[PDB]
Length: 20
Length: 121
Image (cartoon, rainbow over the protein chains, first blue to last red):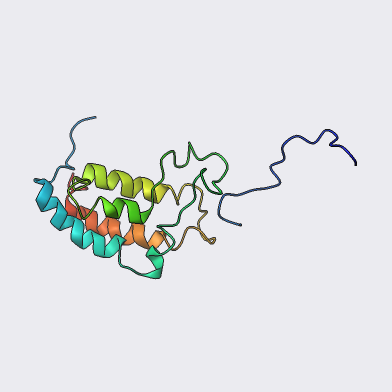
């Protein structure tokens, strides 16, 4: 949307350097 | 606590035992290439690094103080080595792209520290 709407932080599934 | 044996004998005699274990942990091989380029909250760190690492190092740092008389005592050396290992072990899975290039350093140095008498008793 135009402005943020209830987003906050998001882990988005992040497993240290075992993926990036 | 007490009842331990990680002093071996003298700081210089340690620089010696440290050499052979340097050949193992630091064999200038691909297994020791990514160890000096770990991760840290200062640069692309990983979620929660105070319970799985707290104070990580780079194989090049502990080496800059290993050849010298800074970390000749297995207590200090094994401390950074072990932590430098845990820095890439507590969350490196058991067969992914993180727990491998360092697992050969943990298995090759753990055999060279006994000789260093850090594991003497």
